[PDB]
Length: 35
Image (cartoon, rainbow, N blue to C red):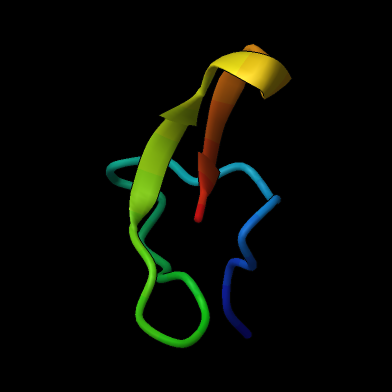
């Protein structure tokens, strides 16, 4: 159970992204997802 580099990610979602990526803003996705 982890957030991939494409799925939304809240700064307080409580979960973490896969591998070792963080939650950044994606202009192209006009939202906030991991990378």
